[PDB]
Image (cartoon, rainbow over all chains, first blue to last red):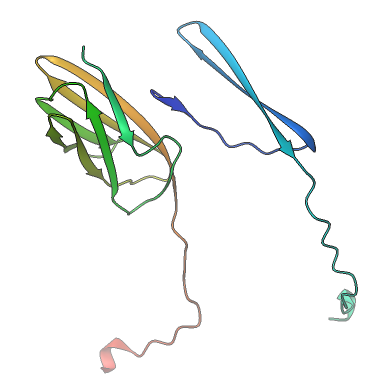
Length: 59
Length: 105
């Protein structure tokens, strides 16, 4: 989304490590690209071992 | 023409339709008149002071609310715009509500 005072976007990181987000913008035949790197990490595994689950087919 | 910028709200903010939003801006010089519009919605005359002005707007359509503030002074007209992320409000149906019959009251 572009406005006269700039703009915004929503992005979804895919790979862990250094997410390299690039924003490119063209106006009046001039194109300018900027980029910012963010430290993206994997989420907590949160397995919750010891969970008891009833059989699906016996419901 | 004169310089014009919109102080608030910031570009890319959060909003919900049906809730009044305050748009305040500062101008280099006093404006003869100014209008505030929300995309394709009806425009409203905005309050103008020597240091800028303000208006109150009502978003209608969800998605990207494109608020445009236009101002004319001394024959020079300058228009600025800011886009805000407007989302639909929570459905909050409250299923399971018991309601007595209206006609039996």
